[PDB]
Amino acid sequence: ADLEAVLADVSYLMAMEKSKATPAARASKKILLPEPSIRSVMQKYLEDRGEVTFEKIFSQKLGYLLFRDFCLKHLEEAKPLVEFYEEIKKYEKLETEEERLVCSREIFDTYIMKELLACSHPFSKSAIEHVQGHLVKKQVPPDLFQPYIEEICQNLRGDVFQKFIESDKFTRFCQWKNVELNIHLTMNDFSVHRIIGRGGFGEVYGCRKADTGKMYAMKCLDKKRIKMKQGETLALNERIMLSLVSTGDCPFIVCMSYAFHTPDKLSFILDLMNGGDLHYHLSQHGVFSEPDMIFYAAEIILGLEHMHNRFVVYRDLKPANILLDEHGHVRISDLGLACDFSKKKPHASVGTHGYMAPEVLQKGVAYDSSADWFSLGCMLFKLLRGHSPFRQHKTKDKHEIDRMTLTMAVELPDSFSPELRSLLEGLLQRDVNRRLGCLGRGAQEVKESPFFRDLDWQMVFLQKYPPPLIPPRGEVNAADAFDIGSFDEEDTKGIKLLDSDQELYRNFPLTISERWQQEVAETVFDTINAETDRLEARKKTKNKQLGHEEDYALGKDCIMHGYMSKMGNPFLTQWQRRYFYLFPNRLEWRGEGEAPQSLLTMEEIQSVEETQIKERKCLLLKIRGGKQFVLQCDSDPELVQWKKELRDAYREAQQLVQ
């Protein structure tokens, strides 16, 4: 290969491998948390939608981390409870009874027996007796301590949670949540490496997120090409499907973290399966063997089960769409042609010739998730033979392959064991009502098939089995960027994107909370937290020494307060950032911090409405008498809450004054 390609590959590989032992060091940009005063607005914003309950926070990764570290360091009473809960959770992940026996005895002695002996145990007799009855019989199921989990959560829900909310670590949670809700991604935020694939409406590049360093796969769709091929509906459907299946914990599907668009591209951020697709590895390694294909079939069956449980039908199932991760475990990747059959069963012949179900290939006849099982059979057949059960592209014409609707699968006796012959005979049935997986419970009908009789599906979900193939660690595991190529830019000439077209993607951008929180927790949570803490320590010392504290008790009846930019003065600085206080009768206004002063009285307000200025969202207040004020906030949540609270305040004040 030429020098440029070699350099691109080396840069991509080094960025992928850099600082594996210290993920925090991979970030080139830094997350700047807002000031601790943010909680005055963010608390109301979260309360107004009921998000400050114990379950909501404790179920969030960052919320859980902050609550845990508060209990373990700033509340002695809650320390044993959190320690017990955490060790129970650790125990639940033990995979063998030989280890669970000792772990459970240690947990019992440490957190139950000693407290019982000291008579300090606060838990109910029921949980004690349940655990004692299970253990006296030598039973160590993973659900041993579930009653203790419930009771620990009940105890933490009490004054412990209120103390946490009143603490300075709920302020940190508010800061992190505000940082989350203000995610506005652009192509600048990512360091895009060499192209790794192409197809559909655009290309796929490996990329590193700037402010966390986590490696992602950026899938870009060109808006002009989408308009040219009338693909707006498909482009939006792909986002719907990705957001539908990403919300969860399934490790068998390429999950989406973010979605955004530039003026000309639609971009999805997905998991990076640096091992490459299974078709490339099949070509390099050759036909797999039955014990090897057991692994792939089991993993793909679990993935399809996850998708089907959500009523999504994966119409294009090929070896090319199956991506191997670093360690060799597979995932389903391309949800471009996926559809939902819960509302109405599709009827379009969408797929790839040689892997489409007979009812999919038939015109007009509706079909359901039943399609994915025929495609699974065809795919498993390819892994063992190098081609679909019906002729390949180089062996027959496209419509000659379509004669799959007028024949029956060969079902070779040589390369297949009788169990596999039965499995493929079930999966390649012409009649949907008789086809395996298309009757009864669905995924269970296949999972219980004889070919998987030896397989323990719990270990499949836990991914304990050794992959048959481990992708090379020193290669990109993809075709050369010259081979992948690029779309012809001339094809888009004559295509113009109207404002009515950019309106189709008004609501496109998206961020998934759990995925972002997990990324932050893995990468830069502790570093940022420490830096933030140092910054507030510095500023607190400065304020204490020089006076002008952060706030003088926040007044007597302040509804809310926070920074806002008094905007729009031509003869002064446009961004006159200041600190504001809201009261039921007036809105006060403070300078650098010496003394607050009144800016406005609610009785004067005529209306409050949002407006766009300098391509930035702002708040417009119109005043009885022709006066007006413009205020600009920093995070959409600040703007939303300020709008809501100002509106409610003046409406109530004027209605009462009526």
Image: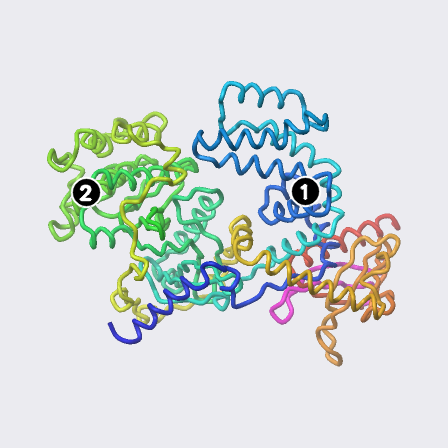
Q: Identify the amino acid type marked 1.
A: Gly
Percent position (x, y) of residue 607? 76, 58
Residue, disc 2: 384
Q: Residue at x 17, y 39 (%)?
A: 404
Residue 344 seen in render = no
On-image quarter of the N terminus: bottom left
Frontmost residue, 612 versus 130: 130
Mark 1 element type: loop
Numbered label tally: 2
Q: Residue at x 38, y 60 (%)?
A: 226
Residue 449 located left or right of residue 260: left
Q: Is 299 in the magenta?
A: no
| Earlier-in-chain disc, 2 versus 1 | 1
Q: Is 623 in the magenta?
A: yes
Percent position (x, y) of residue 348? 31, 43
521 up-or-down from 111: above or below? below
Residue 153 located left or right of residue 593: left
Give the label, 2 or 1, closer to the camera.
2
Magenta segment boundaries in residue numbering = 603-626
Frontmost residue, 503 versus 478: 478
Main SS of the magenta part reads strand
Percent position (x, y) of residue 489? 33, 71
Quarter-wise, where is residue 585 in the image?
bottom right
Frontmost residue, 130 versus 480: 130
Which labelled disc corresponds to residue 50? 1
380 up-or-down from 476: above or below? above
Quarter-wise, where is residue 97 in the image?
top left
Q: Identify the amino acid type marked 2.
A: Leu
How far is disc 2 from disc 1 in space, using C-alphas?
54 Å
Residue 575 seen in render = yes
